[PDB]
RNA sequence: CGAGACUCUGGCAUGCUAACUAGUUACGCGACCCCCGAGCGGUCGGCGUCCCCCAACUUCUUAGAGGGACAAGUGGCGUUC
RNA sequence: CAGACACCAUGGUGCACCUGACUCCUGAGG
C-alpha cells in the first residue's frame, strides 16, 4: 500500500483554517475558511517556495467564517459564519449576490448540492434549513432534527438521490430525504458530541465520528450498521477519498489515515513537536479535504498552514 | 496586575467542568456558546470569564486530575489502576538476622531465627 | 420615607424592602442576580446500547 | 524614496555616531528616517516606546515649553526646519551630523545621586544610562536656545543652530557643555 | 487641520489596497501592506484615542483647582 | 455586607435591519459653463446650485438588535496552583 | 552581615443611655 509524502505547504492565513474545499473543475483551486472574518481563494502554482499565491479575498464579516463550500464549477462561494448569517459571493470577483438572513445565532455549516440550487445549512439555533440561491428559504426542518446544535450538514451525491446527512451534539446522525424532508434513518450508537460526518463519493457508505474518536461505518443505502473502525482520539474532520476507499481522520495528536478496503493503517502523520508546556503544546488538525482527483490531500491546521501531501508508493 | 478572577467565576467553572466534561472543548469560542446552553448568566463579560477559565481547566484536566478539582470518571480510573501489590507478604523472609530481643519475641512464639550479636561503637546510628 | 410628626420634633421612618423577585416572578427587576448563575442538568453522552440503526 | 527616506530638504545619509556607548538611542536611519517627524503624538504609551522615537523627533517635542509655546508643534516644525538651514550655511556639512555630534559632546558620563552621610552634603558618584544622557542633552540644548532668544534679537532657530555648532566641536559658548562639565567634575569629587 | 491630515493619509493608502483586493490582484495589495506596516504609521488599523471626559471639581479633565492650607 | 461583580459612556463591527424633518454613492449627466487641463470638438475630470428616477446604499450621519477581550493562541516562569 | 545613624518644648471641655404580645386587617363571598 501507498503512503503520503509532503509535497509542499500553503501559507498566509491569520487564525485557524477551519475548513478547506476543492472544486471538481479546478484541482488548482483551494477555497479556505479561516478565523479572520474573510475567505481566501487561492490559485495553486504547485510550488516549493510556497504552493500557491492568493487570487482573491472575499471581504468581510463580523465574526469568523466557520465553513465554506463552492459550486460544482467553482464560480460562486457559499459561506456560513458565526455572525448569524450565510453569504453568497461571486468567488472570482467579489460582490454579494445575497445575504441569507433567517438565523439569529451562529451558522456552523453550509453545504451545496451538485445541481447548485439546494443549499442546506446547520446552525446552533438547532435548525436544519433548506434554501434556494435567491435567499428564499424553502424548508425549515425542525422536529427530529437533533435535540441540540447541528454541527455539520453534508450533501450526498444528488444524481443518485438528494439526501443530506446531518450530525448534531445530541450524539445522533439523521439522514433526510429532501423534497419531502422526512427521516430516511436515524443512526443511533454514537458516543459524545459529533464533530463530523462525511458521505462516500457514491453515497453508499457513511462515516461518522466525534468526541469519542470512533469512526463508525454505516451502510447509507439501508440504514444499517456495518462495523466500527478504531481511532481513540477526537475526530475533527473525516473525508473519504474520491477514487479509493481510504478514510482520513484528523485526530487530536495526529492525522490517522486508513484504508477501508482492505483494512490496514496507511500512515499516521505526526504534527507533534518539541515545545513542552505541556497543556498548550499540541496543535490539532481541525480539517481535511481530499482533492478532486485524489492525488493530493489538503489538511487545514490550527497553526495557520494548509499542508499538502501527494501520494507516492 | 489588574483584573484577577473572582470567586463567582471559579465556582461556576468547577460546576460546569464536572457535569459537562465530555461536551466541553478547549476553544474559547465554542465553550462560550456551550455556557449559554447549560446556564443562565446575566452578563457577557461574566460568561466570558467563566468560559475562559473552563478552557484553562480543561487543558490542565486532560493531563489527569489537577489541584483543587476532580472529575468523577477520572477518580474511578485512578481507583482501578491502584490495585498495587508491593509484597505478598512475607516475602518469604524466614530465618534471617533480627535484633537480639526481636529474636526472643520469635523464640517465645515457637519460631526463632538467626540473630545479630555484639555492640561496637555506641551510640547506635552514630 | 415618611415623616411622623411628634409633639417634640419630627422622626424619620425609612422603610426599604428588597423584593424576592429578580430571577422569577416573572422575571423580576433587571435580570437574574449579577453574581448568581443557575445550571440545568446533563443526563446525556452515555449509552450502553451497541450501534444499530433502522429505517424511519 | 523607499530606497532611502530623506529629510524634507536634507539627507539622512552620512550621519555617524561618534560614540559606542550612546548607540541605540541615537538613530536617524537605523530604521527611523522620516521626511517629517510625527508618529501618533503619544510617546508615553509604553516604556518600550522611547526607543522608537529618533533624536530629531525628540528635539522637536522638547522645544515646545513655557506656557504660550506649549502644544504648538506646527510652529516648532517650521522653526526647526529653518534651524537646519542656518546650520548648513554656517558649517557646510549635513546638519544632522552636527546635531549628533552635539548630543554626544553634551551628554554627561558620571553624575551624582543623593546618598546619606551624616546629614552633611555628600553624594554618590554614579554613571547614568545612555537614554538619560540623550534625554538630558536634548533638554539642555533646547533650554539654551530659548534662553538666548528671550531678550535678544535672534530667533529660536538661530540660537538653536548656534547652540548645536558650539557643542559639536567645543567653544565654551554652549550652555549644554558648561553644565555637563559641572556635573562630571562634581561626580568625580564627593565621598 | 492635523486630525484631517492623518485621516486622509490612512484613507488613501487603504483605498488603493481595497481596490486591488477585490478587483486587481492580491500580490499588489499585499506588497503595499508590507511596505507600509514595517516603518508603521497605523494606516490599516484604527487609532483608539478619542477625547477623555471631563469630571467636575477642576478647570480641566485631570487638572484640579488649587487648594489652600493653613 | 462594602468593593469587585454590576451599570452608563468612550473605542472595533464596508456583517445584520432601516432612513424624503439625515446623507452618500452611482450613473445618465445636461444646464448655469469656465475652458482650468486633456481631447479638433462633441466629450471626460471639476467647488457649488440646478436636472432628478420605478436607481442603489448605510461607508460617512443616525440608533436598534449582534459579535469581539476571556490573559483567548503560543512560549517562559510559579507550590506548575 | 562587612559605608556614614544631629537639636525639637508647650497646650482645654459636657449630652455614648436600658422592657415582651406577627393585621394593609381582609371589608363581592366571608
Image: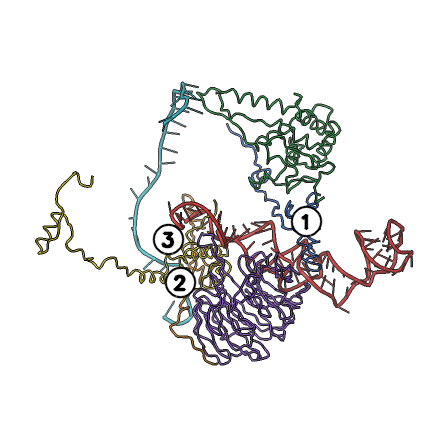
Chain colours: A purple, B yellow, C orange, D green, E blue, F red, G cyan
Q: Nearer the viewer, residue D125 or D160?
A: D125
Q: Percent position (x, y) of residue A276?
A: 45, 52
Q: In which image quadrant can residue B71 be found?
A: bottom left
Label 1, secondary structure: give it.
helix
Left or right of D117 in this view: A116: right
Which chain does the residue under circle 3 lie in? B
Circle 2/circle 1 CB separation < 8 Å? no
Which one is in front in this view, the residue at disc 2 or the one at disc 3?
3
Co-location on one chain, circles 2 and 1: no
Residue tagged by mark 3?
B67
Residue at mark 2? B19
User: Is D150 placed above or below E40 here?
Assistant: above
The residue under the point 35% across, 62% down is: B72
Look at discs 3 and 1 and give the one toward the viewer.
3
| Residue designated by label 1 | E10
Front residue of F44/B89: it is B89
At horizontal 16% and vertical 52% (from top left) the residue drawn is: B96
**Other-residue count near label 3 (Cα within 10 Å), few / some / many at <14 / 14–19 / ≥20:** few
Q: Is residue C32 above or below residue E60?
A: below
- B12 horizontally vs A27: left or right: left
Q: Are marks 2 and 3 on the same chain?
A: yes
> Alpha-carbon distance for marks 2 and 1?
51 Å
- Residue at horizontal 56 percent and vertical 23 percent from the top: D184
Quick one: A24 or C45, which is closer to the camera? A24
Task: Residue B126 in the image: state x and y as whole percent.
Answer: 20, 39
Amino acid at each position: 500500500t501507498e503512503q503520503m509524502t509532503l509535497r509542499g505547504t500553503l501559507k498566509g492565513h491569520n487564525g485557524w483554517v477551519t475548513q478547506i474545499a476543492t472544486t471538481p473543475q479546478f484541482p488548482d483551486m483551494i477555497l479556505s475558511a479561516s478565523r479572520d472574518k474573510t475567505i481566501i481563494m487561492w490559485k495553486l502554482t504547485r510550488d516549493e517556495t510556497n504552493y500557491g499565491i492568493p487570487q482573491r479575498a472575499l471581504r468581510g464579516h463580523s465574526h469568523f467564517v466557520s465553513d465554506v463550500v463552492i459550486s460544482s464549477d467553482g464560480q460562486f462561494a457559499l459561506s456560513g459564519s458565526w455572525d448569524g448569517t450565510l453569504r453568497l459571493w461571486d468567488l472570482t470577483t467579489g460582490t454579494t449576490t445575497r445575504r441569507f438572513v433567517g438565523h439569529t445565532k451562529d451558522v456552523l455549516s453550509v453545504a451545496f448540492s451538485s445541481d447548485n440550487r439546494q443549499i442546506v445549512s446547520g446552525s446552533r439555533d438547532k435548525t436544519i434549513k433548506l434554501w434556494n440561491t435567491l435567499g428564499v428559504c424553502k424548508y425549515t426542518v425542525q422536529d427530529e432534527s437533533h435535540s441540540e446544535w447541528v454541527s455539520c450538514v453534508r450533501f450526498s451525491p444528488n444524481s443518485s438521490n438528494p439526501i443530506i446527512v446531518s450530525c448534531g451534539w445530541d450524539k445522533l446522525v439523521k439522514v433526510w430525504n429532501l423534497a419531502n424532508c422526512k427521516l430516511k434513518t436515524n443512526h443511533i450508537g454514537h458516543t459524545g458530541y459529533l464533530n463530523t460526518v462525511t458521505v462516500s463519493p457514491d453515497g453508499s457508505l457513511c462515516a461518522s465520528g466525534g468526541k469519542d474518536g470512533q469512526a463508525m461505518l454505516w451502510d447509507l443505502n439501508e440504514g444499517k450498521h456495518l462495523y466500527t473502525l478504531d481511532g481513540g482520539d477526537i475526530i475533527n474532520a473525516l473525508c473519504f477519498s474520491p477514487n479509493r476507499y481510504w478514510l482520513c481522520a484528523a485526530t487530536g495528536p495526529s492525522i490517522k489515515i486508513w484504508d477501508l478496503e482492505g483494512k490496514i493503517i496507511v500512515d499516521e502523520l505526526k504534527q507533534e513537536v518539541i515545545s513542552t508546556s505541556s497543556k498548550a503544546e499540541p496543535p490539532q488538525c481541525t480539517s481535511l479535504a481530499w482533492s478532486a482527483d485524489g492525488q493530493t490531500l489538503f489538511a487545514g491546521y490550527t497553526d495557520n498552514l494548509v499542508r499538502v501531501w501527494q501520494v507516492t508508493i | 496586575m489588574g483584573r484577577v478572577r473572582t470567586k463567582t467565576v471559579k465556582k461556576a467553572a468547577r460546576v460546569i467542568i464536572e457535569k459537562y466534561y465530555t461536551r466541553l472543548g478547549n476553544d474559547f469560542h465554542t465553550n462560550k456558546r456551550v455556557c449559554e446552553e447549560i446556564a443562565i448568566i446575566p452578563s457577557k463579560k461574566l460568561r466570558n470569564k467563566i468560559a475562559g477559565y473552563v478552557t484553562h481547566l480543561m487543558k490542565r484536566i486532560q493531563r489527569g486530575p489537577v489541584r483543587g478539582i476532580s472529575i468523577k470518571l477520572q477518580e474511578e480510573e485512578r481507583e482501578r489502576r491502584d490495585n498495587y501489590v508491593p509484597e505478598v507478604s512475607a516475602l518469604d523472609q524466614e530465618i534471617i538476622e533480627v535484633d537480639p530481643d526481636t529474636k526472643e519475641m520469635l523464640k517465645l512464639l515457637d519460631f526463632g531465627s538467626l540473630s545479630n550479636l555484639q555492640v561496637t561503637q555506641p551510640t547506635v546510628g552514630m | 420615607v415618611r415623616h411622623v410628626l411628634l409633639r417634640q420634633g419630627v422622626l424619620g421612618i425609612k422603610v426599604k424592602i428588597m423584593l424576592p423577585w429578580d430571577p422569577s416572578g416573572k422575571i423580576g427587576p433587571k435580570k437574574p442576580l449579577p453574581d448568581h448563575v443557575s445550571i440545568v442538568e446533563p443526563k446525556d453522552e452515555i449509552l450502553p446500547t451497541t450501534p444499530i440503526s433502522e429505517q424511519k | 524614496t523607499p530606497d532611502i527616506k530623506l529629510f524634507g530638504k536634507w539627507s539622512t545619509d552620512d550621519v555617524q555616531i561618534n560614540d559606542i556607548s550612546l548607540q541605540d538611542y541615537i538613530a536617524v536611519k537605523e530604521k527611523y528616517a522620516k521626511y517629517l517627524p510625527h508618529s501618533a503624538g503619544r510617546y508615553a504609551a509604553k516604556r518600550f516606546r522611547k526607543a522608537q522615537c529618533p533624536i530629531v523627533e525628540r528635539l522637536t517635542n522638547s522645544m515646545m515649553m513655557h506656557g504660550r509655546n506649549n502644544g504648538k508643534k506646527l510652529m516648532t516644525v517650521r522653526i526647526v526646519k529653518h534651524a537646519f538651514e542656518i546650520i548648513h550655511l554656517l558649517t557646510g556639512e549635513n546638519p544632522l551630523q552636527v546635531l549628533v555630534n552635539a548630543i554626544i559632546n553634551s551628554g554627561p558620563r558620571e553624575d551624582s545621586t543623593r546618598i546619606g552621610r551624616a546629614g552633611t552634603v555628600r553624594r554618590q558618584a554614579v554613571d547614568v544610562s545612555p537614554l538619560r544622557r540623550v534625554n538630558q542633552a536634548i533638554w539642555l540644548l533646547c533650554t539654551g536656545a530659548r534662553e538666548a532668544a528671550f531678550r535678544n534679537i535672534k530667533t529660536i532657530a538661530e540660537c538653536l543652530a548656534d547652540e548645536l555648532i558650539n557643542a559639536a566641536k567645543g567653544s565654551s559658548n554652549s550652555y549644554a557643555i558648561k553644565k555637563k562639565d559641572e556635573l562630571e567634575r562634581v561626580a568625580k569629587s564627593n565621598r | 487641520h492635523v486630525a484631517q491630515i492623518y485621516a486622509i493619509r490612512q484613507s488613501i493608502s487603504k483605498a488603493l489596497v481595497a481596490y486591488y483586493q477585490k478587483y486587481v490582484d492580491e500580490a499588489s495589495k499585499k506588497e503595499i501592506k508590507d511596505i507600509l506596516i514595517q516603518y508603521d504609521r497605523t494606516l490599516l488599523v484604527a487609532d483608539p484615542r478619542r477625547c477623555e471626559s471631563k469630571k467636575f471639581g477642576g478647570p480641566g479633565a485631570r487638572a484640579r483647582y488649587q487648594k489652600s492650607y493653613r
